[PDB]
Length: 356
Length: 197
Ligand SMILES: Nc1ncnc2c1ncn2[C@@H]1O[C@H](COP(=O)(O)OP(=O)(O)OP(=O)(O)O)[C@@H](O)[C@H]1O
Ligand SMILES: [Ca+2]
Ligand SMILES: [Ca+2]
Ligand SMILES: [Ca+2]
Ligand SMILES: [Ca+2]
Ligand SMILES: [Ca+2]
Ligand SMILES: [Ca+2]
Image (cartoon, rainbow over all chains, first blue to last red; front, side):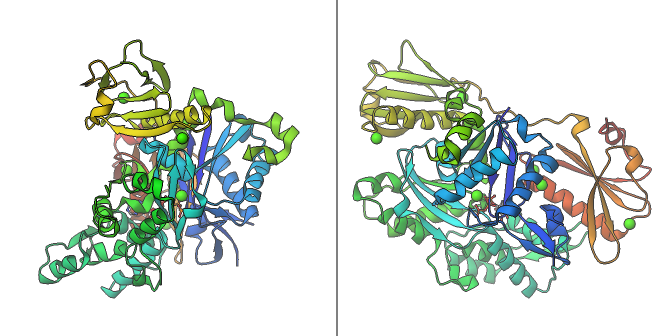
């Protein structure tokens, strides 16, 4: 069996190739005293630790803490011996060459993996949608990326980035639920905000009409029941929170929203291929899960697209984990064993064989 | 049926002896030289769509990238696509996918103590056995498909609150529906005690 680890900025997804879902999902956080605590324990021990994200905007930045992530992935969450399994890693858009030799070197010399491979998250999600060509909107926990892909190859010059994703939406939802008169300080109370985010929020088709509807009645209010029978009541906050993706000014960001960054990404590709990207907008990542987001994207890219351009937004049902599921298929396909990098080649060519 | 068609079946490409019919539950790679078509059935699964797309790029890079890849949505085929075949048609065939639902044996289950001293809520792993459930704390039994919140007779109201919430997050992480079961010490069902080895 092979192992698939999809390392994100906020969440590690890991499991066995062939599984339809990742069986280990834990925060990509390491906490050191103000010798190390990793994952959920790091979060839970928030009051007395310094929490660092080793991956920022999908790129690995703290290597020491990343090995503690990987150590924790292997030994604490899946309880496997990495010496036993080929391991498939994923990588962000624009990941520098040096980072990924370092992913390779650590894999073979620290964890003694028999074989490995590094796949690109955006292409995995695109293939998983049934496409070799498209523009992926990848909205995760810490970063939102527009990744144009032409026949299997991302166009690095046209890739756009929005320093905004699920963790800012959680924080913003916490802020405005506080303005309703609630408090979220303990670990359990912070999970309630995030649980409310993932269950009751939505992207409105037309924002200002939704605000009017929310003001003139309690039609859109919804109640979140707490274990002790309490109720947390939420109104226009359901759609004000993910609206941030389209109006980054809600959190003080002077940036274009996700619809504009999609249009800007397409417009930076050659005129010949924009027709294929306008018609193949694929959503992936945990923050593309809000009900209503595709219909909203469709309406907004239609408003920015040239006349007679065909616009299609695809939001596959499994996009929460589409990167990881893609890697589960890849590492489980007879046809792919060719490009497993065995320890033998790394002994000969060094870390530089990964680019090849 | 002039062009060469590879029918996706169970993570492999089987080339048909007589192309033309396309199953709504499946995926196909239509190889016509400098043009390569992904026919994607509307009820196909993610493993099938994936191999189709990945194989196409491999076929395309096999021919120095000169080939043109296109995607066809099944049931909305362009007329020029259908005329590629002597008599094209649509069927309800569906070869099952390769990806499996994860299943856990009882001995893979994990038990977790939830204890709050006064300042912070602890979450620790404890040996997997009935003899680990102490009456003073709340214990969370992760049974993959089932999550049990075991409330000791002397647990704090906040340990039962918090332990309940982290059960909700177990269910949020995990695909499908997980049954969270709040059980009282001295009232726990047979099915709970069976979830230990
Ligand atoms: N149903 C849902 N609705 C809204 N947001 C969700 C939902 N489920 C998960 N999320 C959010 O998605 C985020 C995690 O997604 P993902 O794993 O794709 O991000 P990542 O890979 O950790 O980060 P990045 O992709 O930015 O590097 C979390 O913020 C989570 O709250
Ligand atoms: Ca990610
Ligand atoms: Ca988890
Ligand atoms: Ca099928
Ligand atoms: Ca080509
Ligand atoms: Ca206690
Ligand atoms: Ca669930």
